[PDB]
Each structure stands twice: as structure tokens, then as C-alpha cells.
Length: 380
Ligand SMILES: OC[C@H]1O[C@H](O[C@H]2[C@H](O)[C@@H](O)[C@@H](O[C@H]3[C@H](O)[C@@H](O)[C@H](O)O[C@@H]3CO)O[C@@H]2CO)[C@H](O)[C@@H](O)[C@@H]1O
Image 1 (tube, rainbow, N blue to C red):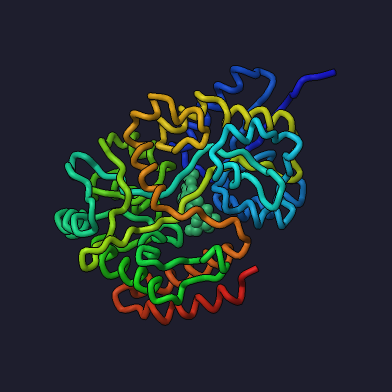
Image 2: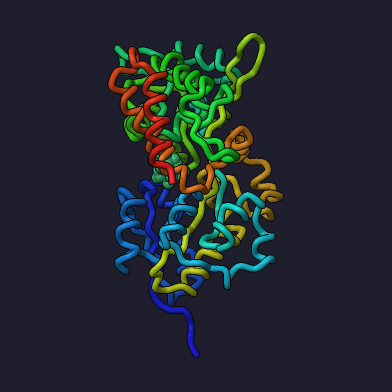
């Protein structure tokens, strides 16, 4: 007879300030179970690192990411099924979309701990009323834009997911998960991309890089940032008094066109080749179904609980940041689990790379047509 012993190794791509929150939870857990070491290990290119290490027996026990990898990782045999651990009682602890995010074709491979998307994070010392329409957003942008003094109207990391809200504001889509077809060359999608680079890019420092954009906001050199819960401890460490609201509707002849960001469910995944399964299960189950664990992720970072019970906690119900991300998620599209999405993301990031070579003059329509076809050829 025995106990669970040893180590649980968890790979991730969190930056240090987000990680701190997760490490303090690990430390609590290790206080609860002194015979179990929880070890977090940062990977620059986590998806690449897992693909390479998992099959060779060099991968971790667990890893953290949004849910959309679960389809392609399972098809590649890179995950460990946990069907034997999942029960209806456990499933019923989670919101249905978290219930669905944690499985692929009938097998469970993870536990869910949050919902997320990007939203406007605004600095209350620079913006006293956040924008409820794109027009008010643009006026705030105009008010603060002053590149000569290294001041910009907004901070916004640029990549497929980060600008999907705007790309998809006018009925466009990267991918229709009904028909399972990319939508890059739909006029409404083209309209959304042009809108980003015509209406919003001119107010930015002209770089798509994540930490450069974020640092502009953290340094008070932009009044607003488009980012997710994963960035919130960075905002807090910078001493900024902030709020969170959804990207507001663009108005066209009195009509609203709501930006529609992609969003997702955060999962702790079980990796194929896992060495310490029962210990890793116990930690994950704790992390995802203990009230104080989930309350801590939500109150510290703005993560929206998918642990139903805590949604009724007054601590959670009266919290501004979780409410604002929650409002943003209401307009979000849940990322598909289809492995087809892999080439979609590649196609959209490829188009953005070419647009960024010459954003003011690029032929966005023809680029998008070009990448639609590449996606159509690489989709599987
Ligand atoms: O752009 C294509 C990718 O879009 C999706 O990735 C999203 C994540 O889903 C989302 O969580 C967010 O990731 C951040 C992560 O949460 C945080 O812990 C880490 O420290 O930083 C990440 C951002 O740099 O944003 C990315 C988009 O960058 C999708 O999940 C992924 O498969 C696509 O490749």
C-alpha cells in the first residue's frame, strides 16, 4: 500500500507576473500535501516544445494552455486520457462549455480552470468614461496619440487571435465551425481587416510585438490596452488603476457591429508519457475544483470562473474585473477544437506578416485571398 509521491512537472508559457499567481497556488498545494513537489517550467515555444518532447519520453506530466490545442494534440497521440478519473459529479461542477472544452471525441484529457478573451483594459487616470461605441474609442485614441512624445492612442499586440475581434466585427470569420471552411476571402472578413489597419493601426506605435505593445500601456504611454486576464498582474505590478470593458460596437448608419474576439477555456492538460498520473490528477483536481484556488485565479487575474459554485460567491459577484471580462466573453466566439484551425491560424498570421510590411498601402483583399487558398491547401 502507498501514497502518491514525488514530482509533478507542468510546462507553460506564462510570463513571470502571471506565473507568480500560479506558483503561490502550487505552494499552498505543497503545504497541503508535503510529499508532492509541483514544478512549473517555462517554454518559449510551448506548442513546439511539447510536440517534440512528449513522443520521446522527455515531456512533462501536465501543461497549461487554452482549449483549442486539444483536438490536434489528441489526434497526434500527445495527450493522456483521464476518462477513468472523470465522473458526472465532477463534470457537473463545471459550466457546460468547460465540460465540452476538456474533451475531444469522447475522451477527457484535461481539467478547465477559466474562461477568457481580450478586452479593453483602460487606465482610469487617463480615461474616466470608457468607450461604448467605436466613435468614443477613436476620440480617446485621437486625444492621446502623440508619437513625437512617444504617446499612442492604444496598445494592442498584433497576431491572428489578438485582432480577430475587429476582423470579425462585420459578420466575417476566420473559420466557420459549421461548414468548417476558412472565411478569409469573404468581403465581410476583408472589411474587418481593412477596418483594423485603417481605423485603429494609425493610432498605434507601429509594431505588432506583444511585450512592446504591453509595455507602452504599463508605462502610461497609452490610455487603453487590448489584452486578456493573463496580463492583469502586470497591470497591477505597474501600479495602474484600471477597468475592463468589451471592445465597443462599430456604428454604421445607426446600426451596431460588435467586435467578436475569439475566446477560450483555459485547461490544464494531461500529457502522453506522463510519469506521475495520480499525483498530477490530485493537484489538477485541486487547482480546478477548490473554491479558493479558483477564487484566487479570478480575483488576482480577472479569469472568469468556470467552476459554477464560485460564480455565486459575493467576492466574485461584486468584482469589477471579472464582470468586465465576462461582458467581453459574451460577444466572443469560442475557438473551435477542430485540427483544421491550425492552418487557419497560420494563414491569418501569414497575411498579417505581409500586411505589416506595408500597412498603409497593402492590398489587404488580395493578400487575404492569397492566404485563404493556402489555408484551404493546408487544412487537415
Ligand atoms: O494567434 C493564434 C493563437 O491564438 C490562440 O492563442 C491565444 C491564447 O488562447 C490566449 O490565452 C493568449 O495567450 C496568452 C496566454 O494565455 C498567457 O498565459 C501567455 O503568457 O501569453 C499568451 C499570449 O502571448 O493569447 C494567444 C494569442 O497570442 C490559440 O490558443 C493558439 O492556438 C493560436 O496559435
